[PDB]
Length: 241
Length: 232
Image (tube, rainbow over all chains, first blue to last red; front, side, top):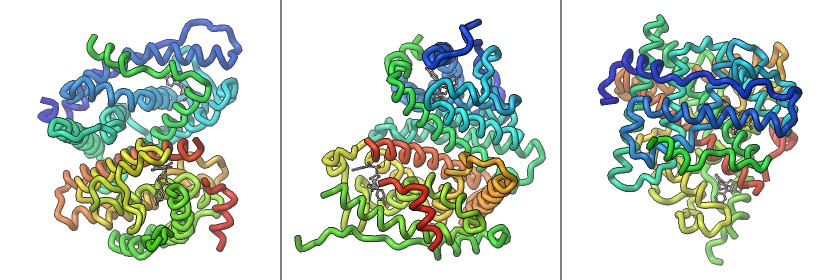
């Protein structure tokens, strides 16, 4: 039934599915150490993950997939989804990252963790780009849903008829979200030329969000913090429950 | 800028004309892996620099910004060329006409099959979409211009002017991509769907490049090398 939705109903579904804004652990000892900041950020990420699974299950077409394919997509996207949410939260705070309403950090505090100021700088540049483009909430939700469906679709094993069907379904849903993004842009008064230029501008930022995730993963490993990454089993458990 | 005055057909012609040749592995037929690929990629890089200088709009940038874009995009450009070459060889990667490898040969290298497998999947996707050569060159130029444009370290007026220019050129390639699709008979809906399909594969190419880099240092041209190669 997901591919029978209209553009306006897809928009409505995605806005209704949005997860809550969570708070960081209240009153930590400030200033931070590297260990304590990572501790606060890990704790917040672990709690956001549960709500991300709930959101994902309400993205039209996601639960049509096998549980295995749902986990693979989440495995592939989760850090990108957390990151774009952060960028969105931070749009109205130039020069700062709004990790939580009670955890607003500027660049110089990313220094307290080794290697994170580079990633801080990349996240701040993405928030500046979103601000420059006047990204709209309805566009953000579509972009976040694209990330979920797209990031892992190309690394499916995907060699049987069923898998061809799964990948085909994902690409049809992704076409529907493109239709939706274009509809939102037409309704706002953009010419056809402006519509296609803005769609491309938004999808190309996704490549930078990928980059940021890859570099973030690198450092969640460089700091010997691989047990911070949600396992296949954990993700599967959250999906079934 | 001359780039911003080009029609879609003039942009495609420019990019097709700039295409580099398909090089051969130096393997001697009448007579090992990583060196064959490194030697090949080294020779490909020289051609890439001269290709880049022919992408409309690229030479309007400062040399420093040209280098930054090449630094950020060179492995993704190599990869998309590989994937394009291998399109008509399902299950195989055509590194060169005399170096056609399948999974089994990817496993032998401690240079992983993980990346081999991701490249094959990109080739399958291109095949499945009937990717056209005119679309390919557009995509290769979008990688060059886009991959580095969010990581310029400067905030001078010039840096703002440079970023704006890159996005205007990128807008011209979008237009070009859409025109090609309209000329081919796609509906307005099919045009924007296919454009999105193409651009979202670029997120996977970025992923493969990042996994390839982390394998490469598990050889990469430095800023100074690229700069030297540029002013020539």
